[PDB]
Image (cartoon, rainbow, N blue to C red; front, side):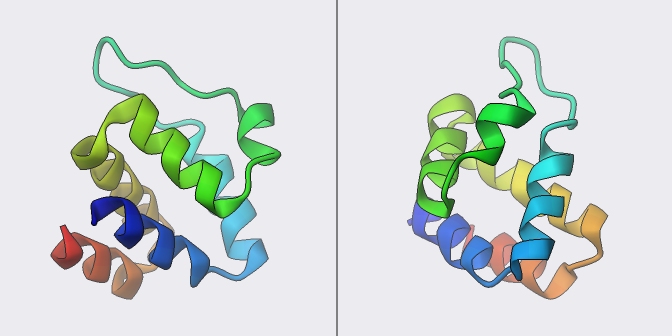
Length: 87
């Protein structure tokens, strides 16, 4: 149910808002022991696979923190707060 929360919120993004979201998530520095997903692999991922891939890579809590943070950094803070509260 954090997985579905990420999904919903991502699905609310215009496809322009999405590319941007994806592009900047791919530059966020990560806690030790976690690996970035290369931006190319990232780009050819639909919303659902993107969501799962984040959760597989970073686990549910971290993945949500990451997303929130990339959103806040996008100033999309309704969607940020929704997810935030949703987790």
